[PDB]
Image (cartoon, rainbow over all chains, first blue to last red; front, side, top):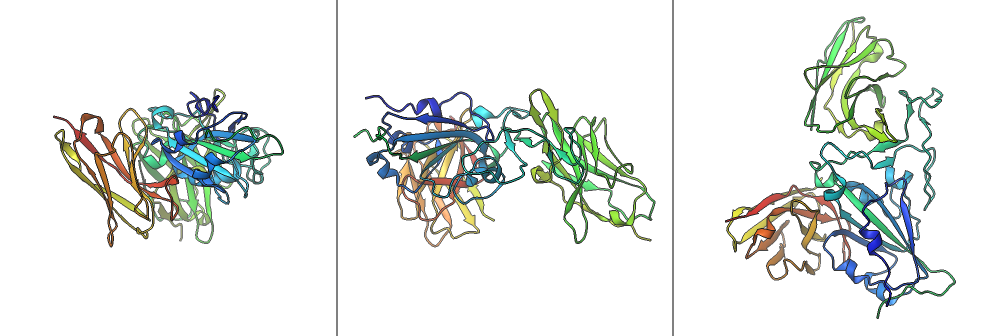
Amino acid sequence: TNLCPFGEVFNATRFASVYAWNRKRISNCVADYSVLYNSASFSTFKCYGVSPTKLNDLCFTNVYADSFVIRGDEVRQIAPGQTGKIADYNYKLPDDFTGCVIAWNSNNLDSKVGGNYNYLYRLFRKSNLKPFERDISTEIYQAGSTPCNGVEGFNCYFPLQSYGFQPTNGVGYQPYRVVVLSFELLHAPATVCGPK
Amino acid sequence: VQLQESGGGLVQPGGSLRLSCAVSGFTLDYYAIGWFRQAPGKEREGVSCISSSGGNTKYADSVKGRFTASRDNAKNTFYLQMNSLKPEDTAVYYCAAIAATYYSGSYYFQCPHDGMDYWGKGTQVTVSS
Amino acid sequence: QVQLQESGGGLVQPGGSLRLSCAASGFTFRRYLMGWARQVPGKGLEWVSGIYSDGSTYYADSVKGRFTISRDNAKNTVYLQMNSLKPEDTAVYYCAKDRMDGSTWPERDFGSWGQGTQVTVSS
């Protein structure tokens, strides 16, 4: 019985930044959700609209896997009805989200002495991001009265900000990898079910 | 990491001052140091922002031409020289640090208010006669 | 708001018993998941054990049998007791306050983190 390749998502060598969050579509397979529960890496496993036990007994036409990296104290923003810089400007979940949120500490892989600057998050935007939208524009954002023409000044900010992950940083500030599973059920054969 | 503020004083109009900010425990290869101010009755406002190297200095329009930001060559201490002070400049001044942004082979050193990671305790500066 | 303090540990012989203790003031301790998490140097955090508000207990395969977790009543301290320690346990142990009330078995969200102490098992 062919299984859903969850390993290609969780054990990916490189994880995309939060602003440019990577989405993989998983379809037409069977997935055993109990390799997830019975693991100790995952510090955060929370579900909305469904119950972990039910997952084995249900079927879904398509499962989406959104993956990215954020700060520890920012994981609380990956939930419906939350606010903050990440939830407002980078990744927003709809109010009726039905799925599970999985996160684990990745300090051994994404930090380096002196700081790892390759991970960025969006810090400025004209309006709040609509749910499941990924704008990756990098134009200069004008925050003050002075008009901006592409030269960063006191009132002309580059919209992206590096995290600067360090190993010395406390657990609250260490990098966490996040994977969001979304369960949509369309009008189509549901070939994602439980293995029983 | 610890941030200490010093040099707060009372001076006559037109006088000068020098604020110091001691930077300790930062192992980051590239960071930025910003000076902010908070006046009575108003929100916090940016005044200055400098690179760790000290090559790039950015000043707000109000303070431009009167404030000079420099870094010592033998210590990790950053200075904000304030000349020709005006009474409206009275406020509590805060030292703050933030990581620099690396993108596509170019570094940016900015001081966005909401992005600062560490703050100092601040000192009051009053300019009266 | 919430403070977690780690007490115990140090240098223990193999087979030694160490009783780790956290105390948390600043929230109603009675109904919140608590757990101990291990960070062996060279790896990421691993969730050893935790206890829910209703006494449901969770252990890891490595520590199953070896460890016991206790949640105190009329006190805000959780106790973690390790026996027959072996070199593989040399690490730092943290305490964690789940961010939602009345959780069940597979729902864990450890937002708050304590300043974990280091446990050394040499000989």
